[PDB]
Length: 337
Image (cartoon, rainbow, N blue to C red; front, side):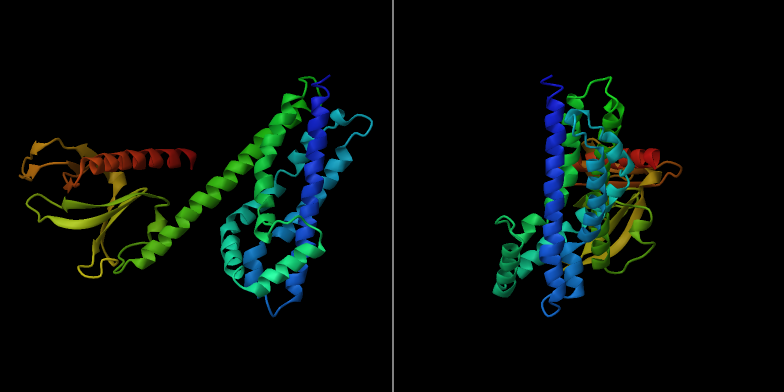
């Protein structure tokens, strides 16, 4: 015991937070959603869609989950409850949080936007006053499922700690811990980083004179970007461009001479066909120039060669690190698929 009891504490706490959480879901879908649907004159279809997301779906799933959990609860002996199986058979269901975790910041945006009108303020205040919730604004209550999907592996780790190796629930609790950890990280990497993938499309559209395929055809991450001087070929003329490095390719633009916030597409490089040669200080061979803070890009199959100058040394280092970064990313992406 006091270990064989601790587990009973963990089980009971989990059950608690689940009942409270499903109650918060109820107070959300009944207290806020319903009333906003009732008032077309204040909330569009688009507005509702942005603010609440798939929360009704979430509630619908949580109901069944908590239901099976209560089925698995042992009243004669709480710490005997076998609850791993529950998480395991509903392991797919949790992916509906992905969506919710994606459109959350947008919900915070529209909420902050609608918190400027006293109408919506008094309305929300009233709604929260009817459903008997705590004095937390709606933006707070809208964070609870992001919290809850993050809390799960924390609660599973604790349950495992006070689970005996011979417990019929041991392997299931373990497996489920692995599962929820996986889920949380998948949510995270997919939403955050692949919506980083989203915004580069915006940037691309901001660019003028676009030549070639869309960048998102081969790439999917902005590594580094900076202004550097460069020379396309030996005896070439020095040009001031702005470089954008992505996985597989590096696009370069020219800044308008007057409207500085304007970019004209000037070409791209296939990094899968180029190696980075770090050039030391001093004097170059034909080519044939003098150098400080400089490096070079060499074609693997061709004798093609390009010259690059940063301004500072910090930038030479940042850039070299950015190329190493790019190669590591290519290797890792092709390895993971």
